[PDB]
Length: 4
Length: 4
Length: 124
Length: 124
Ligand SMILES: O=C1Cc2cc(Nc3nc(Cl)ncc3Br)ccc2N1
Ligand SMILES: O=C1Cc2cc(Nc3nc(Cl)ncc3Br)ccc2N1
Ligand SMILES: [Cl-]
Ligand SMILES: [Cl-]
Image (cartoon, rainbow over all chains, first blue to last red; front, side, top):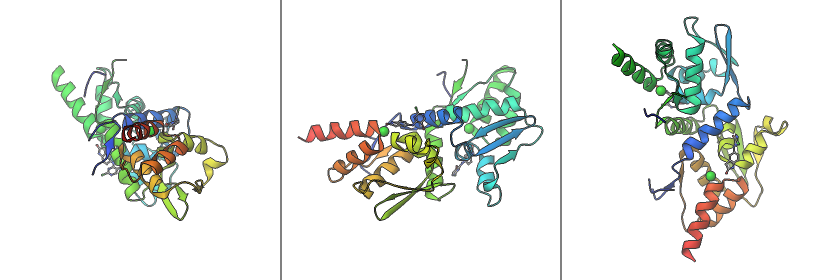
């Protein structure tokens, strides 16, 4: 999971 | 396009 | 093999599937969550959820145009997860994390369940 | 928004759609290319091809279970492109590049046409  |  | 690969292809496909969803094009099922209705593509639901995969591979249920979810399922939690299926983006907030995790467990969306558990563990 | 994103989601969705294709699950159209037949999902074809997008948004053609391609279309070129749609991998070879490019132009698959043109320009 990432900060888009 | 890339070499997978 | 000696194939070449187009890096953005999977993302572009999903973006287009979401555009079809937004315009209600070739949607083939309604998911009923209490008083709310959500139109979607059976194939996308199966590709994202262990529950929908099991439902639409069943010889009788594969032909249903309406699927009713368990009454304990929260429509907002379902909406957030449906958006995630079509976009890869999860709108996870303190106010919705419990409903989202409960819905992802029911839908059998393992990666979503995993991030919810981690976000909950961080706040305790 | 304040969304989080699961990097591998789009790729995992496409992998699952290809698994449904391989097991012939919920395929809803046959594409006829001369003597050959290819089963597929209308939504995936529309998401990958400007030609299929135009075909399945047509109020009459959206309901057809069989689509016949132009007789000039090579079945192997179509097969290579169908595989690309479901996998992001293109099996481009000296022996098939002309058929693949001609098929991608007909199907309106701009990124495929672009790499074919570049590979052809390099060999001249
Ligand atoms: O957390 C998750 C997400 C998910 C998706 C599917 N979908 C499919 N699985 C397989 Cl093996 N083939 C085709 C399809 Br469509 C099955 C299980 C799960 N569990
Ligand atoms: O080279 C390409 C690939 C492609 C795909 C689509 N598909 C869609 N386009 C739009 Cl804007 N919305 C929904 C869908 Br499905 C249209 C044109 C093209 N040209
Ligand atoms: Cl997931
Ligand atoms: Cl393309």
